[PDB]
Length: 128
Ligand SMILES: [Cu+2]
Ligand SMILES: [Cu+2]
Image (cartoon, rainbow, N blue to C red; front, side, top):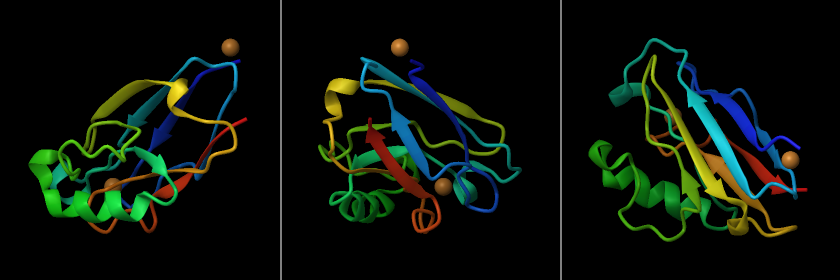
């Protein structure tokens, strides 16, 4: 089974997927994030941040408060399971994380933590 996904965030605050499936036999999983828009990082930055569903609101809230130089994530936030860096127009970032962080049946959310973006830029991740 494949163990990666390619995702885009654009100038309209849209991800091109709202649901990610990680195959149970994967030991690592890779997320390839790209920004095909034209707007720069400081006004339309996008990251891909993963947490349990219950933790998302907290991660997003503290994140936005943390500011651009911290990629809109609270330092040493143990609620973040895995995340890309924050990127603007024309950039791309890839992260690979351990599936051992992803328990069978548990509910996970991915989202962008750039201010205001998470309402429209979010989706589910599950291990099947
Ligand atoms: Cu495989
Ligand atoms: Cu964003």
